[PDB]
Image (tube, rainbow, N blue to C red):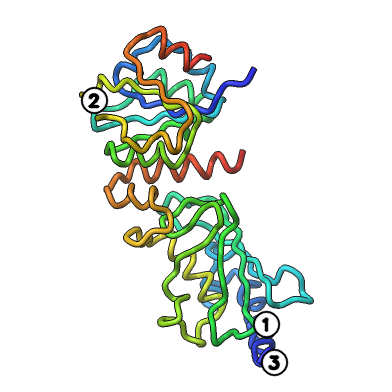
Amino acid sequence: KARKSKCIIMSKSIQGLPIKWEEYAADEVVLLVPTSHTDGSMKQAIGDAFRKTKNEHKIIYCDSMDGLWSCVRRLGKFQCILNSRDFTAVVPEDIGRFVKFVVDSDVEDVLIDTLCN
Amino acid sequence: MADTCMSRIVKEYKVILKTLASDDPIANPYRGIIESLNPIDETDLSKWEAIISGPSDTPYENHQFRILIEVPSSYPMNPPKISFMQNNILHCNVKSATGEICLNILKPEEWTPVWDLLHCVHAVWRLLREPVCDSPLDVDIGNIIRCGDMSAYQGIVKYFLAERER
C-alpha cells in the first residue's frame, strides 16, 4: 500500500541504479541533482520517465550543496536517500529536524529497497 | 474615524472597479498583474480579496495567487494588513504556513496615507519580481538565493507551484 514521501539526492551512484523510474514518477518523490558533484547533466532515461507523465517538475537541479540541503529542509519529505560516498560531514547536523528517515547507503540492495518500498 | 475610512474606501472602490474593468493599458496599468480586487462581502468593506499573476521571468510566472486584505478602522492613517493564503506560495519574504508578508511600504516609518490598495497589491506583486532575501521570513528560501543557487531557487518554486495545482 502506502509508500512514504521521498527526497532523493541524485549523485552518480544513485543515477546508476537499475530503477524503472516510470513506476515512481507519479509518487511524492523529489529528485535533487547536485550539479556541483555530477560531471554534467542527469541521465536521459531518468528525465524521460518523469517527463512522460508530466512529473518533470520533481527533478530539481542544484548549483550548490548549501542550496540543496536548504531544499531538503523546506520540502520535509519523510525519507531522505543519498550516498555520501559520492561527495567525500556530508549530511548537515540539522537534517533530522525536518525529515523522518535518512538512508545513507553504499549498498545496492539497500538503496533499491527503500526507493522501491 | 470609522467615518473618513469608509468614505475613502468607497472612493477607492469606484476607482478600482473603473480601473480593472478595462483592457486598455493606460487606464489599466495592472492588466495581467492584478486580475481582480474586491471586498469579500459588500456589507463589510473592511475585508477584501485580490488575485494577482506572477510577474514574468520569475518562477511565479503563469500562476495566480489570492491575497487577503484587512483594512483597519484607522485606514488610511495605518496601512492595511496584507497576506497570502497559507501554503500557497514560497518566497523569502513570506512565511508560507501563515501567508504573512514582509513588505517595507507597510511599515510605520515608510507608510503614506497617499498609497491605496492598488498600490499595496501592486507592491506585493513587485515583491515577487524583486525579493529582499537579506532579512527573510522564509530562512531556507532565503539561504538558497543568498547562496546564488538559482537552479535550486527556480526548481523548488516550480516544484511547489505545480504540486499545488494537483
Q: Marks 1 and 3: same chain?
A: yes
Residue sitting at x 54%, y 62%: B32
Q: In the image, residue B82 lies at what x, y percent?
A: 56, 68
Of circles 1 and 3, which is in front? 3
Q: Is residue A70 above or below residue B39?
A: above
Q: Is residue A80 left or right of residue B46?
A: left
Task: Look at the numbered discs 2 and 1 and tell me whether their residues touch, using CB distance below 8 Å.
Answer: no
Q: Is residue A100 above or below residue B96?
A: above
Estimate how packed mark 1 is, as few (under 14), some (14 to 19) or many (20 or more) residues with alpha carbons within 10 Å: few
Out of B72 and B154, give the one closest to the viewer. Answer: B72
Out of B67 and A93, give the one closest to the viewer. Answer: A93
Residue that carries the numbered disc 3 in the rendered image:
B3
Residue that carries the numbered disc 2 in the rendered image:
A87
Q: Which chain does the numbered disc 1 sit on?
A: B
Residue sitting at x 42%, y 25%: A102
Q: Is residue B24 visible?
A: yes
Residue that carries the numbered disc 1 in the rendered image:
B14
Q: Is residue A24 left or right of residue B9?
A: left
Q: What amino acid does circle 3 point to?
A: Asp
